[PDB]
Image (cartoon, rainbow, N blue to C red; front, side, top):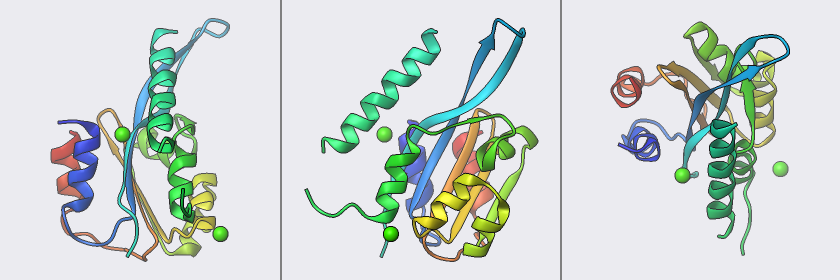
Length: 169
Ligand SMILES: [Ca+2]
Ligand SMILES: [Ca+2]
């Protein structure tokens, strides 16, 4: 039932070797100046597997808590472990980047191979590539976006769309 458990069930649910899964969670920001309400994607939770305003305040405190828990806690910090850490404080206006684009258009965005990551023009895909990712997939769901990443080239997953649906819709 927890985001973290669903994320975990998602990637240990066999198939290919995904390095991590993240859930980017919808929140809303009211801009008094414009009278606009903007959807913003922010860290919901994540599971790192490895290789082989009251809402605003709750969100920031939960992330700070999650950063604390992850860091504390003296050995090597790997490229993909770093990317995972670095992702926790990232956020995305709706329409912006791979997560914003997934959500805004109810898309799956599936990027398979280094060339796809840098080629997409998403700064986050680009960032992940720098850190040794070769596949990134973002799947819009009811309350945000599931992102899976792998240092392997993965261009197919039989079950993926079905599991994501059961676990997040
Ligand atoms: Ca967690
Ligand atoms: Ca490096």
